[PDB]
């Protein structure tokens, strides 16, 4: 099961303990219920303090686009600087959350792989309206012109942490503290 | 269910966590990696100098998840003790070999496989595999060629054989 | 089920085989490969000089099965007209471009793709995809670097753009 | 469900058995139960590496590497281990039963014993390496020869407790 | 779900356990056999002199699981009051007849069946267990083997009194 | 889910008021739970009555007879209430109610007809265990019981008061 | 939907027409039902003429080992020369059949994939006795050492047609 | 997917039945038993002295179905040639042993097992069918019952020659 | 896959032309339907030449068995019943229902009259009686012996079933 930690007294499950340290780990497929559970924690965490930084752990293959955007809007709304940390793969919407971190504060561990390409019910016009919301969100953050974003996304390939740094998805590739 | 142990009583798994022992039993997925990573970071915060103990009995699993555990192992300042019971195959043998040098152990009758099991673009399968070549070459001190070649053989190593290859350091029958 | 036409009677696909027309509709696998190869060798028996017309409306499929069809087209002496109707994808575009030079066709609203959709080791998926690079380059006249870079793009092509690349030769609305 | 006994702390009856240094191995052996038994043994040695630990075996066998991991742990810890076969001990379970401390392997009257093996994915060479690993373990504790140990495990049959005692798998057939 | 009683709060089933009552109800498998053995050994530790009460409403179960419970019943020193309510069939009716002599009860409308239902085993091995049940039945019912073998050959249930005349139980009680 | 009252689960409450709910299909698991409840309320007092709420469409014949003989064994008076349909075994546990204390609500449905692995002879010996049981509690002859149980038919609470299956019908 | 061909009037399906040219397209996964049709077709083709060549088309991923040995033995039994043709792929028991053709008559098309690696309910001793049967057969036909065959088959990899020729599995690599 | 042959047109299996060959391939059950028995009786009425051939490639099956075939083989007057291809285990090996003496064959790589593997029936009934198999085996292998029991107790396969030594067949067709 | 023989019929259609009906498998309403159709047809060709019935069955639906049994007694043809493999439940009743002197079995068959373990109890009990009678009539055993033999959960050897009265000849070859 989920292991329990004790400190002096109260007993915590391990994911509640991380939240106490101001850490929100987006480590699964992104869907409406994960968005609900992240947004609640982010909002709770600035309620503690609008200035003290908040940490996100991103090991995700992507997911539902509106759910990732619900998370994205929340990150931008809240005042805290947000550190994005990519430990597993950062793919589809997961990469969008990684690049949306506070500039200069977006990290990745050395062996992660990042992919901005989106995998393959709504109309064509609506699918295509959402794809361009990503473009612009990516161009806003990745700091790549809209066109090269498009070119990079149509390429079904992964990036290395060094590649993603050159591309502007993330800011620092560390191995040790 | 899970038994409890005692004054306070804790389930036996959380008890191992109180002893800085991190169980990595069963197949590795994103669910297991995230849970392992959380405990590793928790235990480092209690002490960046007391050793960490990983028990490994795993048939392998997702590469990115196993790599996520690998990178956390390297990141934390703590010396990490990998212990192998039963088996360590595919990503399992990589986590074991990524223990702190001189502190990677196997019980006598365990089995070790670094050969990977038989969706994404063909070039991505090759890039991830080649990241395994470098990681194994770093920690077994072998060469990339050797690593590749040995990974091409569908077979298991005895603890003795895996000690000569560089995956582990001690085959402890007794304390 | 399948309608019957008179000439003695014959189901409507066997009638196309009488007109030297072979149908590759739908996904490719080993069974389809055995059907397609048998008809191709059979039609060569009737005459190794008169052309064989091969219709393609396929999203691709097993790559080794598709290669079994490609080798058989190249093997037989008969010139082979390829006709893409509806759309072409994965192995579909390979067989389309593999037709005899000058006899590669497509209808206006066709929809062609050389990108490959996402249990064997990592290295043999590489050599397989690299075999396709060379087959594509030989028929499209492009450099391996142009082929390799193009196959990375997840997109379909128009019949006119597929002709510009060298996949097919004529975009026919009516003869 | 599981009953609760209260001593004031309240325990599930299995934890209460674990209280008395009793580890239950009832049912098939897979990776999850190997972990749960190993943790119990490792913990019970932490309590005391001198007091004996009692191990209850009613198992039809299971995954081999899971059994080898419980066996390897049994030999690692310093406590003497008393194995008790109730019901049945077949395939890997009988190896855990035979792996008790000499003079401390017991079975109940109606306790069936079987060393024959039932007939992820592995090469052929790897299944034969594991079979011979069991050939050596059984011979070490039963004191029989490899020749005897291979021939016996070739037979699809069960042993009575006394036939197992005569064989070297257990040491005491107790009625009371 | 399971109701709770208060005295401290207990689920009803754990309340029956402090009264020294163990419930063998439902099909008998290795899990059921494991709890029953644990409660029995636990009840012996609180007092090896004071009677334990067993309640049997079982339609049978795994033979080796029933034998594991039976052996535990004989091992411990406590007298065992077995109670059949609803039905006791095959391994269920064996446990009922294996209570302490003079303390095998049944409610008026209960039913008893010693007929057996029809890891897999060899022909020679199902016959060996079939013969153990004969001897076990022959012991606690005081009939000839020849009586037992033929009685189990018939696919029928008996009345409480017919089970009394046969030797499986001692008392058919309506009221205390 | 299950509500809480002040603190106990609501079903754990009714039992403290000496009430038992036989409300669902009767099987071995229901039997044990029920029968353990009955035996525990007798530990409270062998004299304060036990009330039993019955809304069941039937179930395993041995399970119902298991509860039945338990009701007979314990001394306390037992009041049976057919709040809800009493089909088959529920209707059985009803006649079993202490003479004079078998009630029902107005729109209840009662049926003694049995619904359409054993031998062919055993089922018959069971169908006849039931014949004697209603004939004992409904005061009827075995013939009228056997003939009525052939009818795939429900009784309304007044009818079954005439039959003898219950004693009082209550609106309040 | 199997097309039909006519001769004049005799209407065959596309496969019965290939059988009539003494060509048997043994493709797809090999099991007992595949074994039978292949055994029969081969046997039937010899009854028409024990001198004219027989042709096999192999596009198979492998399959049940005993079924491939049934086909193998019949290929050897019939006096006819057998021309094996690999199109697409021939792995595990497929590649064995491809190597089992008459010396100087085992072909492959330019893009075929050939593998002798065996992929990952019988005892361990006899899964190994089968593996050694494959060693001997592979070495008899490829004219390689036993040891060379063993270690080549533990490498999980495919061969190209022109490496398979160098190894001894096939003789000729045709483009026309 | 079953081919036809001409002679004037047969599916290939009926062609084999025309050649007095009866196929027993796959698991043996009541449907196999009925079809095999009907072919045996049909072949006897065509000629009660021409030999009949059986092709055995079976892992075994239901015991009563196999016995129904065994008794029919013994009933009919024809000599019966048994040919083992692939494997002959459990009831498969009994039908193979129950051929006319001197007419029991096997191919080189075949495998043979008499060990019985592990309507539902009582204990006394399995041993009844089991002892009944012992006596049929001794009957045709000329072995003693004591040899038969202990041999069938071992979970293993025989080579074609080790089975010939034991009395199951008479001949191995070596190339 | 059913073979065809030589004017070309499948192996099973061939075995009807030879006045033979084979109940090889479990008995249900569909089997009874197909069996009874054959029996009435075989009587159409002639109701004097024998009809040969092959039985390798573990039983099945009782009414379907009784439907076949009644048709057997109705048609005038003498019916040779043959048990190969086994005959249990309704299978043994169809076997014992053969014409006196013409009920056979091969040496290694097993025969069972025990009935293995929706309707009411009265109705199932009532068909048991029915089987009780049919068994007593053809084995010529008394009802008392019949019902005691079917509470027993066991099979008979062909020779044992001959002295019980379920068959007449245990033969190895003609
Ligand atoms: O941020 C808020 C917000 C609201 C609020 C209202 C009352 C008390 N506080 C509140 N706080 C602070 C807080 C306290 C406690 C916790 Cl636990 C968490 C957060 C209302 C508006 N809402 C807007 C919003 C922002 C982003 C995403 C969504 Cl979907 C919605 C923000
Ligand atoms: O280690 C950290 C980290 C961060 C952090 C942030 C705020 C407060 N503390 C933090 N601590 C200490 C801590 C105390 C208590 C607990 Cl319970 C857990 C951790 C953020 C950076 N991150 C880096 C990292 C390394 C390896 C794997 C991953 Cl995925 C991530 C480590
Ligand atoms: O083409 C052939 C071939 C062969 C052949 C052998 C004997 C008689 N004819 C034969 N013919 C002519 C034919 C007549 C009639 C029909 Cl119906 C079909 C074909 C053997 C070799 N093989 C090579 C081959 C090429 C491409 C793919 C594969 Cl898998 C195999 C081609
Ligand atoms: O025995 C140990 C061990 C280790 C350990 C580390 C830190 C704290 N304590 C530890 N103890 C004592 C302990 C107390 C309490 C509990 Cl609950 C569990 C264990 C590490 C090494 N390991 C080796 C081992 C042997 C057999 C099987 C396995 Cl898989 C592993 C033994
Ligand atoms: O009975 C025992 C036993 C043992 C034991 C060892 C140490 C401490 N106590 C122990 N007790 C008393 C106890 C206290 C508390 C509880 Cl909760 C349960 C039991 C060891 C031997 N074993 C034998 C046995 C008998 C019957 C069935 C089986 Cl499978 C096994 C009985
Ligand atoms: O009634 C009993 C009974 C027994 C008993 C034994 C020890 C302590 N008390 C006991 N009591 C009183 C009690 C106290 C406490 C509780 Cl919580 C519940 C009940 C044993 C016999 N049994 C007979 C019985 C009757 C009906 C159905 C069944 Cl299956 C069994 C009744
Ligand atoms: O080859 C045979 C064989 C037999 C045979 C018997 C009677 C008539 N003919 C026969 N022929 C010629 C034939 C005619 C027609 C057809 Cl369609 C096919 C073949 C009997 C022996 N058997 C041996 C055998 C070899 C390889 C595999 C197996 Cl499993 C079995 C070969
Ligand atoms: O062998 C027989 C038999 C019978 C028969 C009756 C009428 C016409 N012929 C008959 N023949 C020859 C035949 C020709 C043609 C065909 Cl297609 C099939 C068979 C009746 C008796 N029976 C006995 C038997 C033996 C072995 C197994 C069983 Cl289950 C049954 C054999
Ligand atoms: O026997 C009959 C019967 C009827 C019949 C009617 C018209 C033409 N013929 C008929 N025959 C001879 C026939 C020839 C050929 C064939 Cl294929 C089938 C039957 C009608 C009555 N029926 C009674 C019956 C007996 C047994 C079982 C059942 Cl369910 C029904 C018998």
Image (tube, coloured by chain):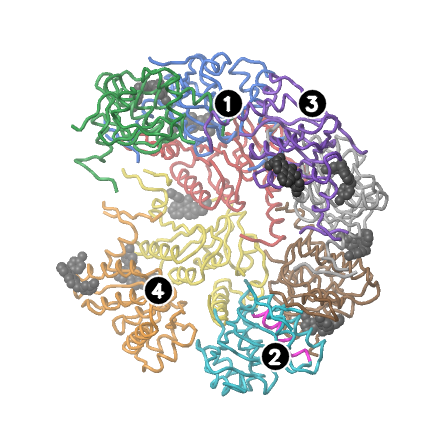
Chain colours: A orange, B yellow, C cyan, D red, E blue, F green, G brown, I purple
Task: Find residue F121 and name its label.
Answer: 1
Is any part of residue D150 visible from this angle? no
Please report, as a chain letter, where disc 1 is located: F
Q: Which residues are magenta?
A: C63-76
Circle 1 crowding by C-alpha within 10 Å: few under 14, some 14–19, many from 20: some
| Ligand 7 quadrant in view | bottom right
Q: Which residue is mark 2?
A: C53
| Both marks 2 and 4 on one chain | no
Mark pair 3, 4: CA separation: 75 Å
Mark pair 3, 2: CA separation: 74 Å
Could you say which is closer to the camera, residue D139 or residue A104?
Answer: A104
* Residue F108 percent across, percent down from the top left: 26, 31
- Classified by dominant secondary structure, the portion drawn in magenta counts as helix
Circle 4 crowding by C-alpha within 10 Å: few under 14, some 14–19, many from 20: many
Mark pair 4, 1: CA separation: 62 Å
In this rendering, the label closer to the viewer, 2 or 4: 2
Please report, as a chain letter, where disc 4 is located: A
Mark 2 secondary-structure assignment? strand
In this rendering, the label closer to the viewer, 3 or 4: 3
| Residue at point 71%, 80% (across, down) | C48
Mark 3 secondary-structure assignment? loop
Q: Is residue A144 above or below residue A112?
A: below
Q: Is residue G56 magenta?
A: no
Is any part of residue I150 visible from this angle? yes
Do the numbered discs 3 and 2 sit on residues whose CB atoms are within 8 Å? no
The quadrant holding residue E43 is top left
The quadrant holding residue G41 is bottom right
Q: Which residue is mark 3?
A: I165
Circle 2 crowding by C-alpha within 10 Å: few under 14, some 14–19, many from 20: many
Could you say which is closer to the camera, residue I74 or residue I148?
Answer: I74
* Residue F81 percent across, percent down from the top left: 25, 26
């Amino acid at each position: 099961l989920i292991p329990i930690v004790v400190e002096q007294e109260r007993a915590y499950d391990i994911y509640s303990r991380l939240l106490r340290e101001r850490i929100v780990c987006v480590m699964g497929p992104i869907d409406d219920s994960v968005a609900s559970l992240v947004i609640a924690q982010l909002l709770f965490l600035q309620s503690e303090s609008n200035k003290k930084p908040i940490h996100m752990y991103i090991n995700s293959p992507g997911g539902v686009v509106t759910a990732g955007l619900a998370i994205y809007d929340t990150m931008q709304y809240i005042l805290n600087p947000i550190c994005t940390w990519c430990v597993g793969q950062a793919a589809s919407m997961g990469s969008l959350l990684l690049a949306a971190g506070t500039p200069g504060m977006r990290h990745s561990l050395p062996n992660s792989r990042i992919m901005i390409h989106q995998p393959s019910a709504i109309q064509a016009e609506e699918i295509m309206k959402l794809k361009k919301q990503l473009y612009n969100i990516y161009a806003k953050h990745t700091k790549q012109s809209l066109q090269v974003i498009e070119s990079a996304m149509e390429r079904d390939r992964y990036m290395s942490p060094m590649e993603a740094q050159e591309f502007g998805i993330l800011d620092k590739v560390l191995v040790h503290p």
